[PDB]
Image (tube, coloured by chain):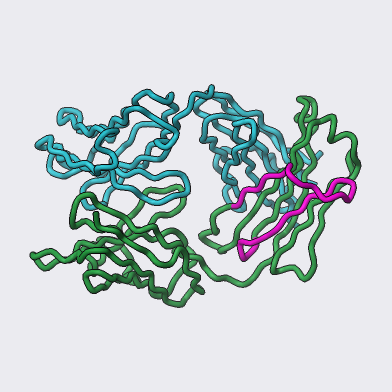
Chain colours: A green, B cyan
Amino acid sequence: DIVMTQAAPSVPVTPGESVSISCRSSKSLLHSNGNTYLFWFLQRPGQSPQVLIYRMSNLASGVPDRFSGSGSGTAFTLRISRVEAEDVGVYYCMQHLEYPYTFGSGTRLEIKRTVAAPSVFIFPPSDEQLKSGTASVVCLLNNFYPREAKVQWKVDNALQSGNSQESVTEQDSKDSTYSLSSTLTLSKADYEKHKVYACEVTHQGLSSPVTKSFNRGE
Amino acid sequence: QVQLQQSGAELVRPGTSVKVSCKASGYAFTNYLIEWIKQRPGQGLEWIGVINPGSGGTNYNEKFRVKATLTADKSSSTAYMQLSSLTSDDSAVYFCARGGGYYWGQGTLVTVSAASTKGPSVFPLAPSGTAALGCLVKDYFPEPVTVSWNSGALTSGVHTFPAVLQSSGLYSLSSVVTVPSSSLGTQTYICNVNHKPSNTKVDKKVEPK
């Protein structure tokens, strides 16, 4: 088969600047008809892929003129000029010369915005959930940048281990931030043996960790 | 305007077969090829194969020759992909695309599992000049759950997080929204949760406690 390689799993770009995304093939994609059968696609989160460039260097119908493609037959570059916050997503190359058709592993475009510390919020378990016998304590880290952020749970000031789970959003297409939720799960019986619940957050935008907390029963 | 409409999400048992469809409209179905693509969760694109709906001719990626069968019905402008001997490795989103990749179907999620369907419990994340509130959608199977706010009227400031798979084998997700603190006494906030696999529709009002 033809192996397609994308050397960068991600590339950071400040809005307004240009970016190049590379792809390589293990065989020439040049056909004897003179065309090179290399395609570039964009895939936004939760959506189907969308074509950007066909036959290595041609802009597909309806794609902004800030996108361009070029290449040698075995090495290819997708160039995006004046990168916008909305350009976040994964860019894949694909060869359409020989069966089986094959795709590169994708390059995520990460928008480099100003560093922003998270706005932290803590939510105790609802009384509705407590009636059912379980307690979920939620810590929200909202609209921060960069992606990396650590959340530590403390119960009666004691650091927790093995009982939390985190989920992170995709980079926002307008403001270029991430949000994160951490859930600490205990039984209702164990939740009621402690008074203080806190989430401590570490992030580049904070000079020292931020803690949000509540006392059970307010 | 062209459309490739794919069949809905499928929860299917291991060892069985699943048949997904891709109905074309807005163009002459028999004049263009249909290609099939697999995307494992959080992973890249894998090409399965292609069919010419006019001739019935097919080509398969060797990796899918045993598992996949591509067919097309000219009378209903529908392309079909059947996958056999299903394993958890077949759990993925499958896309159909018109040859060349300008037009694509919306994808069909296939979950291969012997686990039972289970609807979620929805709990409020009550708000404490901006306030955050939300809903915790707990203990459901399979994916997906969708969440809207105020029947779709509230979209700004909403973040619906990816679901997490718990140790129990059940999923959970949270959806949050930030709103002006001044609105908490005058505006009703409702999270509309839909878990189509279990026919669960919950419209939970989230109030300051």
Image position of A5 (left or right of B183): left
- Image point (12%, 43%), residue name: B31
Residue A131 seen anywhere in this rendered image of the structure = yes
The quadrant where residue B163 appears = top right
Q: Position of residue A23 (x, y in %)?
A: 33, 66
Comparing B158 with A199, the one in front is A199
Image position of B23 (left or right of B124): left
The quadrant where residue B187 appears = top right
- Image point (64%, 70%), residue name: A115
Image position of A142 (left or right of B101): right
The magenta segment:
A144-168
- Image point (85%, 46%), residue name: A155
- Image point (39%, 75%), residue name: A81
Q: Position of residue B44 (x, y in %)?
A: 40, 51
Does residue B4 show up magenta in the picture?
no
Image position of B137 (left or right of B40): right
Comparing A12 with B25, the one in front is A12
Does residue A152 show up magenta in the picture?
yes
Total marks in image = 0
